[PDB]
């Protein structure tokens, strides 16, 4: 049972979602021929 | 669910494509409007003192968040409420 | 392909194989003169964990051996991409 | 095949595919100007539920 003035004020509401960060360019680097792979010129993490 | 999508950058150095984002959007948002805290919610009827013996205040209405609620006639400023009882 | 030593051997001397469809692994040979430990490292510590960082660790078979190593570098992708709870 | 609008896209521009064995779906395109809802409708109500 109580009270209060009235602004003169402005809601801005919200809405919560959980999401996940993920790369901008969709990819993978496959292969279509058989064989027995024997050069790898990359290591993981650098352009 | 349905998916949304964000358009960031990653200059920084890291936002490793694997983490989660607690995302808090916006929707809607009015500028300069009238306030009577939510719990005043009772059609759709209220209560207004005078004096201090309360004489009601039927209204209409919205739009809430997160326990306020814009008030469109009304009800002006400085007045009297009943949040809540 | 390498010397390191032998670590599996799923085959049987006398056993038919069928390599046309998917490639039957036969012996598994990896390098046991070094080793490398892979610290799972959770999604809230990673803003912090950096490469070359005065690590220490311990074998789940040692009452104090306490190993004095160092972090060597970082993956950019989770432990489920690289090679829920994240 | 249709216009309706686009609803999936499982592919990557740069990606190898292998369609000889099973058929790689590439884009998924279905019609969003109408829709249709599918009321699950349990084994004891169906003697009753009729069309229109």
Image: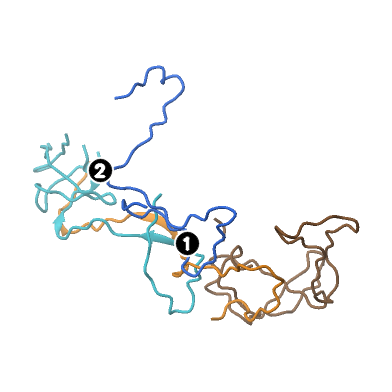
Chain colours: A orange, B cyan, C brown, D blue
Residue contact at pointers 1 and 2, CB within 8 angstroms? no
Q: Quadrant of the C terminus of chain B?
A: top left
At x 27% / y 46%, what residue is drawn?
D33
In the rendered image, the vertical position of residue C4 relative to residue B60, given as above or below: below
In the displayed orientation, state which residue is furthest to the front.
Answer: D20
Residue A7 appearing in the image: no
Q: Chain of mark 1?
A: D
| Distance CA(mark 1)–CA(mark 2) | 51 Å
Which residue is identified by label 1?
D11
Of badges 1 and 2, nearer the viewer stands 1
Q: Nearer the viewer, residue D45 or D17?
A: D17
Q: Is residue B80 left or right of residue C11?
A: left
Q: Is residue A17 left or right of residue B13?
A: left
Image quarter of residue C17 = bottom right
Q: Is residue B55 left or right of residue D13?
A: left
In the rendered image, the vertical position of residue A29 relative to residue D3, given as above or below: below
At x 48% / y 65%, what residue is drawn?
D12
Which residue is identified by label 2?
B39
Dot 1: element: loop
Image location of residue A33, percent across then percent down:
64, 68
Q: Chain of mark 2?
A: B
């Amino acid at each position: 049972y109580l009270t209060e003035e009235v602004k003169r004020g402005n809601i801005e509401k919200n809405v919560v979602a959980t999401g996940s960060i993920e790369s901008i360019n969709t990819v993978d680097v496959g292969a279509q021929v058989s064989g027995k792979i024997t050069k790898l010129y990359v290591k993981l993490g650098q352009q | 669910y349905y998916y949304a999508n964000i358009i960031v950058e990653n200059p920084e150095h890291v936002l490793r494509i694997g983490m989660t984002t607690e995302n808090n959007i916006k929707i809607a948002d009015v500028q300069n409007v009238l306030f009577i805290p939510n719990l005043a919610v009772q059609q759709d009827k209220y209560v207004v003192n005078v004096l201090n013996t309360t004489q009601e205040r039927e209204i209409e209405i919205g739009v809430q968040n997160d326990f306020q609620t814009e008030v469109k006639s009304g009800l002006t400023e400085g007045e009297k409420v009943v949040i809540s009882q | 392909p390498i010397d390191g030593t032998v670590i599996s051997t799923p085959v049987s001397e006398g056993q038919t194989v069928n390599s046309n469809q998917t490639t039957p692994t036969i012996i598994k040979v990896a390098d046991l003169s070094k080793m490398r430990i892979k610290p799972e490292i959770s999604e809230g510590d990673i803003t912090k964990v950096k490469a070359g960082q005065d690590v220490t660790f311990t074998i789940l078979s040692d009452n104090k051996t306490v190993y004095h190593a160092k972090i060597d570098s970082v993956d950019p992708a989770t432990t489920t991409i690289s090679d829920s709870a994240v």
